[PDB]
Amino acid sequence: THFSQQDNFSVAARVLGALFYYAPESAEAAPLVAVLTSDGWETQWPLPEASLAPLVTAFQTQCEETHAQAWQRLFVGPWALPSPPWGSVWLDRESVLFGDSTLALRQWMREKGIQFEMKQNEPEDHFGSLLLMAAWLAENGRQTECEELLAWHLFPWSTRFLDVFIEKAEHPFYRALGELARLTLAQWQSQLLIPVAVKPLFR
Image 1: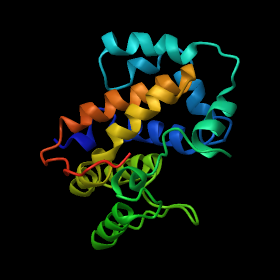
Image 2: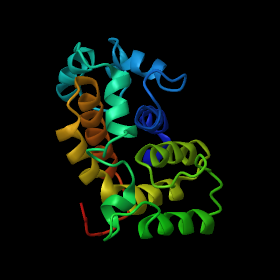
Image 3: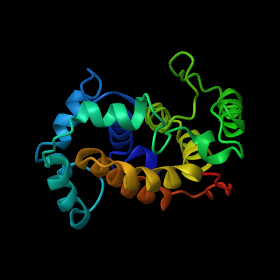
């Protein structure tokens, strides 16, 4: 019955999350770059074809800039990232990392006995970390928590983050990845029984 337990929710969340968290040449993400750059993946993605046809091609579009170089520029640095993948940049009035929305997520994790750990020195509210934790909760049959994560701790900023990211990606693969993410999270959003939390955006 619950939308986290069907339509490839966990599988799709893990794919989107890893491609946003790990480098395209990494052991974690290279196989995923390879699935999205081959025909066939669209058959298993939980969205309709009229919207996937264009992304199939777009994911395969060659480009002088390397996946590795695009990711570096979009997610690592050294310079300012065009769309910072951490919730508190979007939700905290001050746009700092480890901000108030980050604290809210951490407190919620601790109340619900959620033991999922992020890597060291890293804030909990990274877009991909959130998608991997949602996947992980789904797999564990923790549907209520999964829905709360999305409603309360991801969807309030994820659309804004994706909007700016899709507009500034400037690389066919990552722009396609962004659009895929937006279409998919939107679809999930429409399946929630619970309202998305109403929060101002500060970037």
